[PDB]
Image 1 (tube, one colour):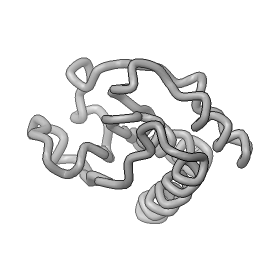
Image 2 (cartoon, helix red, strand yellow; image 1 turned 135 degrees about the horizontal axis):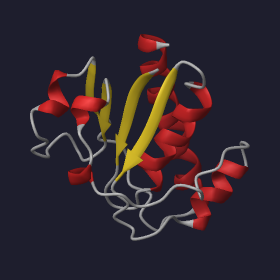
Image 3 (tube, helix red, strand yellow; image 1 turned 120 degrees about the vertical axis):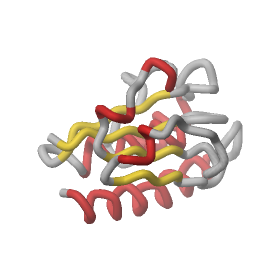
Length: 131
């Protein structure tokens, strides 16, 4: 299928969640992956907020951007604040976006819920373009 990527920074739960919604909502329409995990591990509070909607982001893990090749992912979604000097292969894709969204860092459950919800709409919009 069309290959997709979600690049992560800060508490990477927001951007790996974008992949978690994208595997869920893009199922059988796209192939989807994530990279960067700047929180050095996943964050159980995000897993709980995704369990609250029947999604899993604990099985996800760290793998650096420099080992990826956007030339091999037709649609790439940075979440680095639309201000990172991605190699030019990250631009030639069918989609190149940067969902410069909120930061759940070590926040309340409400931000872990809210950022997830706002991400899910961006995910579903991306899906609406491709799937």
